[PDB]
Amino acid sequence: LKDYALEKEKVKKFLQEFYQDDELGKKQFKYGNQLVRLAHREQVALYVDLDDVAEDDPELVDSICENARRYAKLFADAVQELLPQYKEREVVNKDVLDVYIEHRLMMEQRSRDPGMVRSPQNQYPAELMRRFELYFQGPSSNKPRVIREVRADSVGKLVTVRGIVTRVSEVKPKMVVATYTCDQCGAETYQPIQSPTFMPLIMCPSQECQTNRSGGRLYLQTRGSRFIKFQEMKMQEH
Amino acid sequence: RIQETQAELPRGSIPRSLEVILRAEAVESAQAGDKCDFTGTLIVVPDVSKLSTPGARAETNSRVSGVDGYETEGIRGLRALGVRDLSYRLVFLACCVAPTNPTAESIKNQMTVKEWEKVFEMSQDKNLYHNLCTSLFPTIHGNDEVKRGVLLMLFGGVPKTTGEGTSLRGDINVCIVGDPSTAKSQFLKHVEE
Ligand SMILES: Nc1ncnc2c1ncn2[C@@H]1O[C@H](COP(=O)(O)OP(=O)(O)O)[C@@H](O)[C@H]1O
Ligand SMILES: [Mg+2]
Ligand SMILES: [Zn+2]
Image 1 (cartoon, protein in one colour):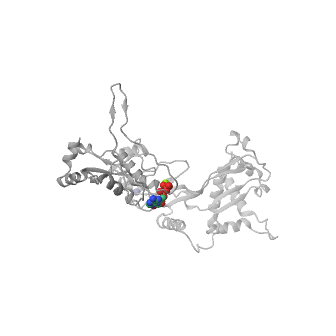
Image 2 (cartoon, rainbow over the protein chains, first blue to last red):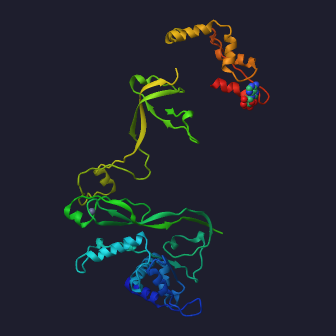
Image 3 (cartoon, each protein chain N blue to C red):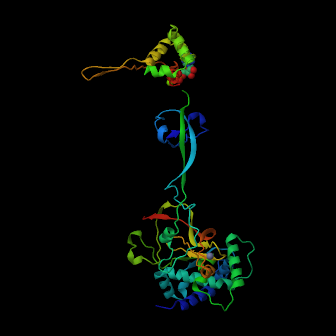
């Protein structure tokens, strides 16, 4: 096993490095331009090719193949850390969600002194402030598999499949993080979701409610919540 | 159970159905198939499986919080605060039921003096055989035989039973067969009305 910090640094340098490919016949900083577009709302998802990474390090590619989800999360965090560096201007036009993000960051700067102790529960969830998605492209060397032969040995791996579509679900919003407001305080509570079903909270974990022992009760909000687009697909063999 | 009448239907709408509740003496009346007026109250009764999605609900005003090992999680927290789902339905309680439009001795006693006068005036007229034919079917031309047959079927015969356990019919059945457009459904509609 390897420490995640070293590989995170390697991911950051890989994102900062490549200059090679250009369509018009030149040498163009592709990932830098992608990141600059990502800084504002000019691109809301990023796709990473695992063929380009293979030039410098194949062990990274293998570890990504066998442990894909952890590496997806690491890539997301690395890109989020890189985003402030490439930012050059404020948003020309922004929507409701950006308004929440800006307001929350502004009051975080207003309140939190650099020296005061902050509880691990007092931080913002990572994915709430984030607004970009990362996806992977299958290796060209990797051979597409067959629906019949994917089994327990393939659970958790990265695979590529070819099939025929038979059933598609209509688009409906899916919850990512739920936002709660206390009955007797101005604090905000965040509940991440990683289950098909979840149980909404009741009492307020905010520090003021704890100190006063007021017993304030939480309420859901839909505006503050984060939602994603979700679809369900059915595939069959050739 | 009661239903909204046809005359109150708007465009392209199915009649509305409502539940009526009778208590004590008013329980007797309002048999099935009737067309009646009700007078009473409109009252709200709770329901169970109305809300597939969370809605309005009750709770307690006491500012009570949990303790370690007894934290107010989902089920225990909901049971501790006495949370109930506010679901409701509309139910009508009736205190007066009447016919919309209103044992020979009983029938005679029910009728007033003027109604009995009219009945007696009708009774001793031979033209009762003729005038009843024209009254029920003013617009249909001819076919007086069918009118007489329908009137005879309406009045009907007398049922009897024998000593061997058999029974004898007392009713009359009528069939009409004809060429198209010979007012064949008009008789059916007039008898229905
Ligand atoms: N003898 C009659 N007198 C008056 N109206 C008549 C007569 N015969 C037919 N009609 C008219 O013609 C139409 C006959 O249609 P209908 O009785 O429904 O035919 P059927 O019952 O054979 O399907 C009615 O609307 C009625 O007004
Ligand atoms: Mg007809
Ligand atoms: Zn609170």
